[PDB]
Image 1 (cartoon, rainbow, N blue to C red):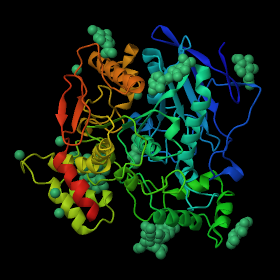
Image 2 (cartoon, rainbow, N blue to C red):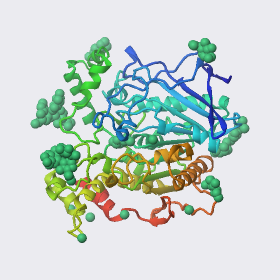
Image 3 (cartoon, rainbow, N blue to C red):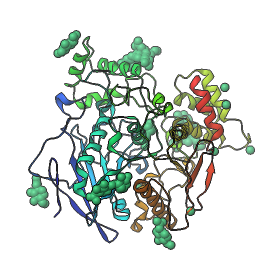
Image 4 (cartoon, rainbow, N blue to C red):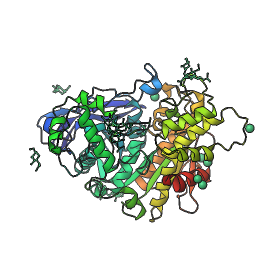
Amino acid sequence: DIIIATKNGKVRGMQLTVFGGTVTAFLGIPYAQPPLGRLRFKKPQSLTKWTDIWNATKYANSCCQNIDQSFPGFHGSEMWNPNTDLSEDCLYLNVWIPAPKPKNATVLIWIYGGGFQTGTSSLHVYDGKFLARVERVIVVSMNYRVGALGFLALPGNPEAPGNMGLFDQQLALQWVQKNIAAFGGNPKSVTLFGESAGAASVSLHLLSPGSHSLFTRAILQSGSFNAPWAVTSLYEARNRTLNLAKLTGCSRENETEIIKCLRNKDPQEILLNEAFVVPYGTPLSVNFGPTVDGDFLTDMPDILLELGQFKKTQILVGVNKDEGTAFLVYGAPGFSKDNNSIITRKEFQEGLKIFFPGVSEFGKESILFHYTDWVDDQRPENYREALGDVVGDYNFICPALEFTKKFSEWGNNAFFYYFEHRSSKLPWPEWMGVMHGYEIEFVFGLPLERRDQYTKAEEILSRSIVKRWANFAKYGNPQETQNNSTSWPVFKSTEQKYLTLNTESTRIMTKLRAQQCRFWTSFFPKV
Ligand SMILES: *[C@@H]1O[C@H](CO[C@H]2O[C@@H](C)[C@@H](O)[C@@H](O)[C@@H]2O)[C@@H](O[C@@H]2O[C@H](CO)[C@@H](O)[C@H](O)[C@H]2NC(C)=O)[C@H](O)[C@H]1NC(C)=O
Ligand SMILES: *[C@@H]1O[C@H](CO[C@H]2O[C@@H](C)[C@@H](O)[C@@H](O)[C@@H]2O)[C@@H](O[C@@H]2O[C@H](CO)[C@@H](O)[C@H](O)[C@H]2NC(C)=O)[C@H](O)[C@H]1NC(C)=O
Ligand SMILES: *[C@@H]1O[C@H](CO[C@H]2O[C@@H](C)[C@@H](O)[C@@H](O)[C@@H]2O)[C@@H](O)[C@H](O)[C@H]1NC(C)=O
Ligand SMILES: *[C@@H]1O[C@H](CO)[C@@H](O)[C@H](O)[C@H]1NC(C)=O
Ligand SMILES: *[C@@H]1O[C@H](CO)[C@@H](O)[C@H](O)[C@H]1NC(C)=O
Ligand SMILES: *[C@@H]1O[C@H](CO)[C@@H](O)[C@H](O)[C@H]1NC(C)=O
Ligand SMILES: *[P@](=O)(OCC)N(CC)CC
Ligand SMILES: [Cl-]
Ligand SMILES: [Cl-]
Ligand SMILES: [Cl-]
Ligand SMILES: [Cl-]
Ligand SMILES: [Cl-]
Ligand code: NA
């Protein structure tokens, strides 16, 4: 029986057997007042004592959100869907700890992706018990509001100010500051880590003065706040808030009256209209995301980044070899997960239309010009490969590299990875390669479980990544120092060295996608 006293009450956890040892898991601790009724669309409110032993013995509700129904029955997509009840009452967090209780353990705090519209901490690929067992760190993860319920904005209006879900993440870091010593944690050694929209969220906590003192270091997997999908403009945000009002018949003249109307709507009506607050959309659409609210985010974040206005600390930033492929089967003509998807030039051009809505005709042509100068015109998989590269370079790889670069220019050590291993167990087709999302299970250590059908080379790759991630958290340096591993150099502007992660031999390379990112980064933002 393990009871820990928190500032708010006692919590009971549960014991788990992991690799012939024991981990204590406290799943589903509340960290804020449920954001129901009058609290819907407001910032999270702090929680008050219970007294009372809260049983933290199962995952809590995931936050309200639309689900992916493109491939029913398919594990590839469905493994990403929520696996606990959806509810507005979703402001909970999990803590895994080594057994025996550690003395002053480094803490890893996971923030999930999901386009800011979906996601939950209770996915099996986010389970923190292998890390706690193997590296003796504390792993913490939290649910935070997504979609309109998390990011609806009527700028400056405390009834609906924007960024509520970022504030939920933030109030969870506060909970770790106040409470993690009780569990054997070190509040002075906390590393935030996240993937996709979770990584962009980590990058914005680097920018937020309210977050500065709530953590030590940061890890960004496939995402940064300068990615083109990560920040909504004040103009867009309003248009979308009002379009939601119109679609739910909540149009008004008094903006606070609009919000009052939206709080009477049932969670489901709001969810069902979210998708149309926008005329055109893409498979990377973030209808309701971060905005500049003058609170969480004080200025346009590109300005903050450029001018050195962020937390000074080390970062670890990486991307996967084939970020863009997963998205091609959510609407690009000629694509399918059930065949090899050899598309034509005309289909490629149509695909650009899906992913670059408007986007001038000249813009789309320039993308076509940069990516289709074949060497050579023979290769039938040409146009199919070019479209995924277009998508992953624009949306993930080039913003990550540009982020790392601008961050490093202010003096801090930074380390960049390029993840090139495709899981032996991937249920997606071979042509999709090293997909977005599929480093996560390696970082969380799932392949350490032999019972599980990953190869030997995969167990070894994972064990090594886990060590580097843990050494980063504890010591600011992602080395694996014992097994003659390749040493991981800092990423500097000028050299831009990065480390490749794969089962065969890991290399030090330079200037990833140099020629492609010159296009996305200097030229395209003009069109
Ligand atoms: C701001 O919104 C307008 C339109 O407002 C929207 O109403 C919503 C209920 C939604 O269903 C959406 O379809 C509708 O657009 C956007 O302009 C729209 O673009 C096309 C033009 O062919 C029309 O179908 C819309 O009716 C038209 N506006 C209208 C109705 O006046 C506009 O793009 C958007 N501005 C942005 C992006 O900030
Ligand atoms: C790979 O499949 C795609 C996707 O669409 C198809 O999925 C297949 C597995 C099959 O069941 C098919 O009936 C299903 O619609 C194919 O794209 C389609 O190409 C067909 C050619 O008959 C067109 O009629 C469709 O409009 C087009 N689908 C769309 C709208 O995206 C694709 O041709 C196929 N390519 C191969 C075999 O290499
Ligand atoms: C726990 O250690 C505290 C200091 O933490 C520092 O050392 C490393 C953990 C590293 O991550 C640094 O960034 C931190 O500055 C110390 O002040 C506390 O008193 C310790 N608490 C205990 C042992 O109960
Ligand atoms: C919490 O769990 C304990 C131990 O299993 C149980 O005895 C106690 O009644 C529980 N409290 C509840 C069910 O609210
Ligand atoms: C709008 O209506 C709200 C509803 O209570 C009210 O509080 C507010 O004063 C009104 N705003 C103004 C000043 O127009
Ligand atoms: C070091 O290598 C041994 C085998 O020689 C292996 O079992 C262990 O997992 C390795 N440690 C790390 C952190 O990779
Ligand atoms: P991520 O948050 O993706 C989920 C892994 N990204 C694309 C989904 C934001 C648009
Ligand atoms: Cl899995
Ligand atoms: Cl060729
Ligand atoms: Cl190595
Ligand atoms: Cl390259
Ligand atoms: Cl160019
Ligand atoms: Na050009």
